[PDB]
Image (tube, coloured by chain):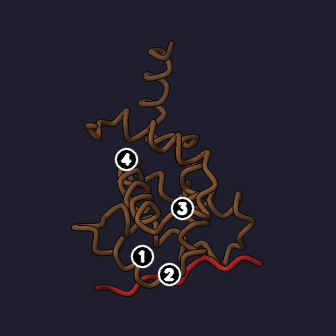
Chain colours: A brown, B red
Amino acid sequence: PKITLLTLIKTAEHWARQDIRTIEDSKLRALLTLCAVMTRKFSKSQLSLLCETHLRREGLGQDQAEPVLEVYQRLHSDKGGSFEAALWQQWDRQSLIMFITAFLNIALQLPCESSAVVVSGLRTLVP
Amino acid sequence: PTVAPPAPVYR
């Protein structure tokens, strides 16, 4: 199947509603890519809001904002999956699972652009 | 390749 924008979102919808703690590593690795690709569909301005929401929902302290925002920033600017590969190599499986699930559940509810002019205009078009 | 940041600590 073609990885269109719609397919990408439907794939995210689907995996957001799964318990991924027992899935094989090959699929977990692919989910990391999904999070990376999906992160890049947010404007740069929305990454702090992504971080703040991640912290709030996961019950993390403000001292965790630096590393969490860094993950989102470095995925957003990732070239050739270099940073993505580093996360896979250097984090334990439990950390990856928790970050991935957290992201997939927040990503579909946050706006992907921040300009009021963009948001207000697009709302007039929604059925 | 690079050096990843630390994973989030739950507490």
Cα distance in 3D space between marks 4 and 3? 25 Å
Question: Which residue bears the numbered disc 4?
Answer: A41
Of marks 4 and 3, the one in the foreground? 3
Point out the image quarter for the N terminus of chain A.
Answer: top left
Marks 1,2: beta carbons within 8 A: yes
Question: Are the numbered discs 4 and 3 placed on the same chain, yes or no?
Answer: yes
Amino acid type, mark 2 = Trp
Mark 1 vs mark 3, foreground winner is 3
Q: Residues within 10 Å of mark 2 (few under 14, many from 20)?
A: some
Q: Of label 1 and label 3, which has the lower sequence position?
A: 3
Task: Bin the neighbour count of mark 3 within 10 Å (Cα to Cα): few under 14, some 14-19, many 20 and up.
Answer: few
Decide which of tag 4 and tag 3 comes sooner along the chain: 3
Report the residue at 29% width, 41% height from top. A3
Is A73 or A93 nearer to us in this picture?
Answer: A93
Characterize the local packing of mark 1: few (<14), some (14-19) or many (20 or more) Cα atoms within 10 angstroms. some
Write down the chain letter for disc 3: A
Indicate the chain on which mark 4 is placed: A
Q: Name the mark on residue A121.
A: none
Q: Where does the image place residue A30, in percent across and percent down from the top left?
A: 39, 60
**Which residue in the structure is indicated by mark 1?**
A88
Q: Are marks 4 and 1 in contact (CB under 8 Å)?
A: no
C-alpha distance separating marks 4 and 1: 21 Å
Residue placed most toward the observer, A87 or A122 = A87
Residue with the mark numbered 2 = A91
Q: Are the residues under marks 2 and 3 on the same chain?
A: yes
Q: Amino acid at mark 3?
A: Ile
